[PDB]
Image (tube, rainbow over all chains, first blue to last red; front, top):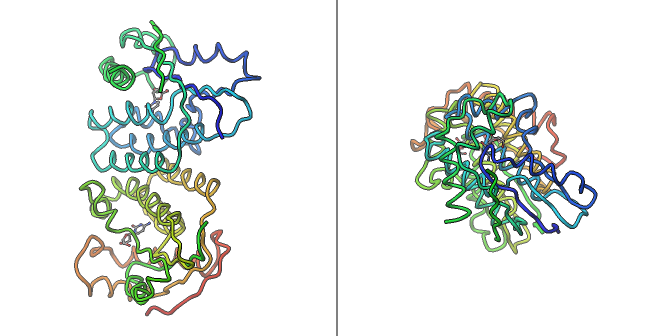
Length: 185
Length: 191
Ligand SMILES: Nc1ccn([C@H]2C[C@H](O)[C@@H](CO)O2)c(=O)n1
Ligand SMILES: Nc1ccn([C@H]2C[C@H](O)[C@@H](CO)O2)c(=O)n1
């Protein structure tokens, strides 16, 4: 029992937070689920996001596992509203962020495989509500400027190359469920 | 929709496999779920059990996460039989095996916390069927002997100290009732 669901997808620095704020005035009639970064930063006093960025070969696995969980919690969360808008999803976690961490060697085969088994079990047990994806398409260099533009201790070591990798993965998934592409440049 | 469920608990080398085999002849009327070791040994060609034992600080986290999943799959698996018997459970994973890996330093705080968030979400979303626990109570020394008397596998180098740690945790849970079980425990002398 889930309302019409829109997912906001795009690279780091694609303006999703700014875009999602346009909907804040409609909170009375729309279910607005911000990406649970605050959950990730305080898993009982542990900042998994910081640990992942600081040491990905060690922390990519637990971090992405906790991402999967929190996204699943958002996807299945109860609301009486007839429209739901989600910042990101279990799908970008899987198809972009986990895939990239596998490709750059931060997730070893067995760790990726464990994450993959969870996704399979989720998809087999739960139909995940996804009616529309709004893809905030950017160029990696503009995304880079947006990250530096905002003070975020965690992401302040992310190379342009990493953003390029995440860009191509969003392109594969979303270009190469209805997808609406917006020029977020 | 799950039948009456019995969970077989106890240390490594407590004789659970031998004990579960006594029920094999009753497969027609009982749902028999062996501990999914074969799944753990072959996660797309990856032996997570071997990797965990060889390098626990690296592999305890993904291993126990996969344990959680496979146990959950067993707990929720469909059967038309009116009795189900399970070798181990999500509860021993949480209360003994994960707790011990946390205490010995193989699971850092953040990794333990991630595993714990999954357990919470599972208990809040799914009532896990558990009607009876049969505790195959052994002494660590006997559990140790059983391991060293059988064929070599991933387990075969676990120190006696590790088995003593797991023993006390099974006692805390199943005898002291210091973990939130609320379930009848039948203790058997598996020595
Ligand atoms: N599946 C995800 C989702 C988000 N992030 C990171 C990218 C940003 O740095 C931050 C906020 O979205 O979290 C991530 O590594 N993996
Ligand atoms: N949660 C669990 C369950 C089992 N095992 C191990 C103990 C045995 O060595 C092997 C087969 O039971 O798996 C484990 O490390 N963690």
